[PDB]
Amino acid sequence: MKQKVVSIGDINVANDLPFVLFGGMNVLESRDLAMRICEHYVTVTQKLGIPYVFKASFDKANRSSIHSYRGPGLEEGMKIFQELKQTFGVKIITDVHEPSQAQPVADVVDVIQLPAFLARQTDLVEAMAKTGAVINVKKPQFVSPGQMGNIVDKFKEGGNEKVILCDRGANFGYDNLVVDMLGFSIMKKVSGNSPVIFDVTHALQCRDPFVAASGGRRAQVAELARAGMAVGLAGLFIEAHPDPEHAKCDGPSALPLAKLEPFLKQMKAIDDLVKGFEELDTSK
């Protein structure tokens, strides 16, 4: 059939409708740090005809604590969004965490997001449904693609149908991740022919680490993000930074802010002749 289509303003994600870029950076650091990162993506998108959704997050919770650089806090967090917002009037995105705060957040951001870790949490499916915004079910590393029609189900069941599926890779043996390009469709088909997207930072993150032959970073984001794009994704998802990120030069991987442009020119041209490619199939 044709692919379902959750519509974001002039942008429309869909599996035969170009890789929309849910670009961005990680932890919402400086109301103005953003800007280097916010503004810089925006230019390029346009130069290439890539649509753009800026990604930013208002919190921490995952890893180190007792405050340890926990991020902006909904209150002060949500302001910074509202700035770069009209500054260059663009589509943003944010992951809630614990129900309540699932509405305020859902006013500055265009595409809310549910953390891989709480996917099977119900009360947030529920508490993101008694909303009606664009949801981005971030896929858990321990869920076979084929269970995603079970995060989607209850979403619609919660009133909310506007869903998106972001794949990040599954774990491979202790501390490692992988991505099977064959998981995409599988997710595509259980998810009412819904839109499927590749998150390469949080993915490649551990994929590069297979210590012995690792024990110390190294990146190939475009080399792995080409694989996804070369199969047929609704979109791509990446985070950037000049000096890899205070939040990405320690946690996951990270895209070199100024290295962005030609990466996309790869992703645009590669993708290019795929959404083109007239539907083929080899089950006969």
Image (cartoon, rainbow, N blue to C red):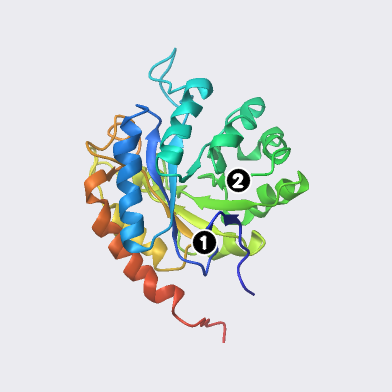
Q: Residue at x 42, y 48 (%)?
A: 172
146 sits to left or right of 34: right
Going by the picture, which residue comes out furthest to the bottom? 284
Secondary structure of residue under mark 2:
strand
Of the image marks 2 and 1, the number of the one nearer the N terminus: 2
Does the image show residue 253? no
Spot occupied by residue 225 in the image (x, y as percentages of width and height): 35, 58
As rendered, which of 75 and 96 lies closer to the eye?
75
Local crowd at mark 1 within 10 Å, few (<14), some, or many (≥20)?
many
Q: Residue at x 24, y 59 (%)?
A: 262
278 sits to left or right of 200: right
Q: Distance between the residues labelled 2 and 1?
A: 18 Å
Q: Quadrant of the C terminus?
A: bottom right
Does the image show residue 89? yes
Q: In which quarter of the image is the N terminus?
A: bottom right
Q: In the image, which disc is placed on residue 262? A: none
Spot occupied by residue 147 in the image (x, y as percentages of width and height): 64, 52
Secondary structure of residue under mark 1:
helix
Going by the picture, which residue comes out furthest to the top? 66
Circle 1 is placed at which residue position? 184
* Amino acid marked by disc 2: Ile
Circle 2 is placed at which residue position? 135
When asked about the image quadrant of residue 95, the answer is: top right
Q: Which residue is drawn at 69% across and 50% down?
A: 150
Q: Please, is residue 31 above or below residue 203 in the view? A: above
Spot occupied by residue 214 in the image (x, y as percentages of width and height): 24, 43
When asked about the image quadrant of residue 274, the answer is: bottom left
Spot occupied by residue 77 in the image (x, y as percentages of width and height): 47, 25
As rendered, which of 81 and 189 lies closer to the eye?
81
Local crowd at mark 2 within 10 Å, few (<14), some, or many (≥20)?
many
* Amino acid marked by disc 1: Phe
